[PDB]
Amino acid sequence: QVKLLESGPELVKPGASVKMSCKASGYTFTSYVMHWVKQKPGQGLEWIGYINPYNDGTKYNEKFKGKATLTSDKSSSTAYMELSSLTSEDSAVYYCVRGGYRPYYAMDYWGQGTSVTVSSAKTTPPSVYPLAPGSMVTLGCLVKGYFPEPVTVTWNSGSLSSGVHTFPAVLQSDLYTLSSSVTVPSSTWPSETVTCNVAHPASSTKVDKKIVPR
Amino acid sequence: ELQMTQSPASLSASVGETVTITCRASENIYSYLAWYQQKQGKSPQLLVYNAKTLAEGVPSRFSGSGSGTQFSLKINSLQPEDFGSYYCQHHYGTPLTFGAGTKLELKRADAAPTVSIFPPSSEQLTSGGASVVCFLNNFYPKDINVKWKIDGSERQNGVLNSWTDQDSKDSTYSMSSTLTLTKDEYERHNSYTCEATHKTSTSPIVKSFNRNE
DNA sequence: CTGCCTTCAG
Image (cartoon, rainbow over all chains, first blue to last red; front, side, top):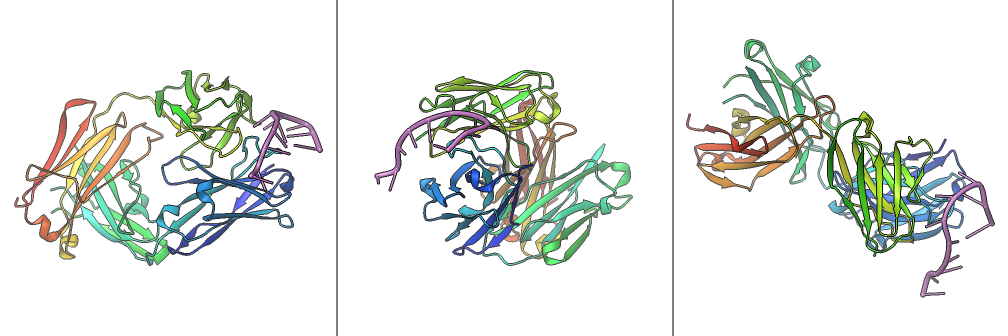
C-alpha cells in the first residue's frame, strides 16, 4: 500500500527558507521518480519538478530553478523540497507525488500536502463583534484581525448547528477575518440568547460574544 | 510549451447523468494524457493515464478517450461522490502542465439568496472601525454579484467577499460581503446598501439601513 | 550539449 507522509504545516517569515519532507513507504522508493506540485488556495495545479531517488538526478520547471531545491535520501526513503527567499506568493499547499517507473510516465500517488504560509505577522487573537439586525431571523459575528489560522466558531456552544454559515477567512493587511451567520426562528431570539463562541488555539484564546438587540 | 485547455470550467449535472469533460492540447501529445480527480479539501487522485487506462481502484464508470490534440473523460451515470474538480495533465515530456480544471457541481432547483445587512457594532465603533456585513445565503446557481452603495454612490474599495463551496446537504451556495471603513468615514454617510444581482430575478435584491435611524 | 523511450519494466 503506497504511502507518502508529508512533514507538517509551516509558518515562515518573508526572506526565509523552508525545507519539507515526503517519507515514502509501500513500494521501492528508488524505483520511481518523485514529483512536487504547488496548489494555491482555490487555484489549479503547478508542477515544480522531480527527483530520481536512484541517482539524485533532478528535472525542474524553469520557473522554480533557484526557488526550489529537490533532494532525496535513500537510507530513509525521504524526498525533500527546500524553498528559498520566501514571498507571500510562495504561500500554498505543496504535494509530493510518486511518479513513474520511467520518469515520463504519469504521476499516480499524491501525499496529503504541506501547507506553507509566508508572513511577518505575529500571533494575534481575534476581535469578535456581534452582528445584530438593524419568519426567520439572521444573526452573525465578525471575527477580525487574527493570526494565524484557524479559528473555530460555534453557536450556543454547538447547540445551534442548523442554519449556520461560517465563511472562509480572507487576509486584511496580513491578518485574517471571517464571519459566521446563524439563522433562527424569531420566537427564539431575543427571547432566548444566542452567543457565538470563537476559539483561536494559536493564542490560547476563547471569545464568547452574546448577540443583543440594538 | 504545452498548454492544456479544459472545458467546461464548470459543469452542472445530476446523479445518473453522463457527463463529458474535454481537454485540448497546444500540440499533439499522442496518448500521453492523464486525469485526476480532486475533491474539496483533499489531495488529487489519478483516474486515467495514457488516455484510456484506469488506475488501480478507479471504478469503470470512468473512461477516457482521445489522441493527438483532443481528449475526453466520460463519467457514465454520476454517483454522489463524483462531484468535485477534475484536471487533465499531459505526460509527454517536460515541463508538465495541468489543465485549468473542470468543477463538476450538483444540480438543484434555483433559489434566490436570503440577503441580510448588519451595521457596525458599538464594540467596533469604540475601537475606531466600522464594518458593514452583508450575508447572501442559500442561493443557486453560484453566479452572483454584490454591489455596495453608500448614499446611492457605488463603493468598491474596502469590500471583501468570501464564498462557501456548494453545500453537501442542500446544494446551495452562500456568500458574505464586508465593507470595512473607519468610524470617521462611516459617520459621513447615512444610507448603506447591499445589492445582489442573481439569475432568479431580473431585479436585484436590495437591503439597506440608515445610520441616522 | 543534456539525447532516445510511454506502464509491471533498463
